[PDB]
Image 1 (tube, each protein chain N blue to C red):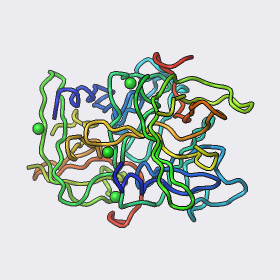
Image 2: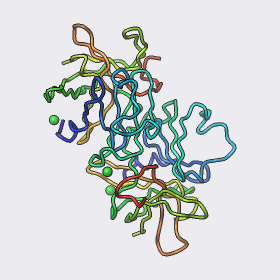
Image 3: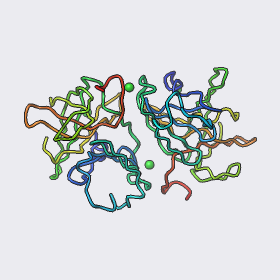
Image 4: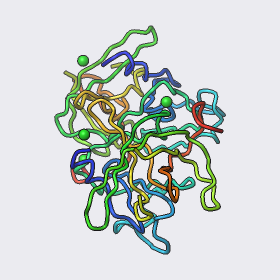
Length: 170
Length: 170
Ligand SMILES: [Cl-]
Ligand SMILES: [Cl-]
Ligand SMILES: [Cl-]
Ligand SMILES: [Cl-]
């Protein structure tokens, strides 16, 4: 992952989020701060906030990152796709983790149904919101945000956009 | 423009629209058929319909074009960018037109304020909805939908997504 791609990964709430474009930010629902009247200084009424399970998207009225090109956001990826989870730590450390993605499904996690994609590491709770990306040609695609990990044994889950289709369970 | 890119350009209402991804379709507001209860066989309540001036986006619940990758949709492009307007005609003829893009502004056109970008051809009314695209590296970006042309003298306008910013007038 190049520096500019890492620059999209952004501290947010109790986790992280990701600038898909100058105005679009995605993150994991459970890290979104509660009881606030603005995000990044913008009043809530100036933001189109779309939340479905553990997937949250903000579309700001203001260009927040005019330095960035738009990039492609997809609903997960095909079985077996190798992605990178672009984890930043509070210290500043970068920890890109390779993951081989599995099935898209609605999965019960900590009492809630979560629409997401599981994968096997080839994480810590503070990492939630980190993007799952993969390279397509010379460009990068984002396809989920980090939502859960097993206590051991190398399974992770990213939340993905809402959407039903023939390749997903359901 | 490659065949797959052309394949996204789709007859719609009194004009055309464009598949940005398997679920996202953009078109020009004035070509959207009136008094219907579905688009492409999908009931309106199953679609997230976002309309701002002459820019209309549909996000379907069903994957309508699962053959397609997502591609980047931006709000217009920098001054001077050479785009291609991917015009299909009812006969099947392809007529890609080169255009050098100008200012993004809210412009009065036929009595209505239209948020769009003007450009100079380097069209017919039935062409409305055709995408304005430009190549970035090895990939293509869409940045507007055809909305208007001057009676002569080689000016065109594409509608663009809502959004204010330092490079646009307003
Ligand atoms: Cl690399
Ligand atoms: Cl920009
Ligand atoms: Cl070419
Ligand atoms: Cl697909």
